[PDB]
Image (cartoon, rainbow, N blue to C red; front, side):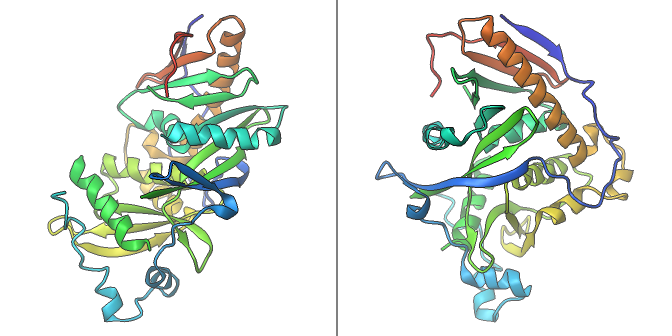
Length: 331
């Protein structure tokens, strides 16, 4: 019924490996549906009916020209205290998205269905000092559903998005191939669209980067995995002054740009434990546990009455799978 399996010796490229072009985590990755969820109307508007959050035009223009139209516009973003005014269910949508796209899945492969956050968590295991715990359900159609079960920093993040974007949430449902045996159907929340480039733009709040600092290398790698799992997507980072909390600089990054910042023949020269946060090793790890997870969840599910399993991964990359009660549903 259960399984304990070490995955620490997973096949992977040298920790110092450098290649100029960023690798792709998924192949043939595409957006298959999108939807806006108006929370108070308990309504999902799909595709042509959804409302795409627009990245402010002054901001799209700033990104395109690498310069502000004028002082008035620049002073509406740069210098603003992202801390002003601080003293103040997702699994349901994934399942509707699955129902809408199921007929289109590849019956010859196992598809993992999940919110993007959990795919990122799984790829991040070798780069973290905390373990991972998730639920993975082998559905009767044999596809697998993944699920689960600092206030100031998080708030300046909402303020930054608030300031750059013209409640409600927006989601892109993407499909991609990981293996000759595995596909992924992922749900991702998109902060906005750059209307000039028709490109999703994910907004991140940050203090200037200190490569060398473990926390920042983790964030940069996560950022890279985050956009790399999508078909088209750019990053827009708002750096704030550490002391004043004022937005000091806005900087756009394409996937190749975040990639280059974390993979060079120069950054790879410094010592480090977590596989030196190499995006290429993350990619190898990605290819590995997903194949291990697929083979094993399928094997265990035939020989069991349980369709749901607790999936765990040590900080030593030891994988643990045990059946969860057939009388318990995690929503």
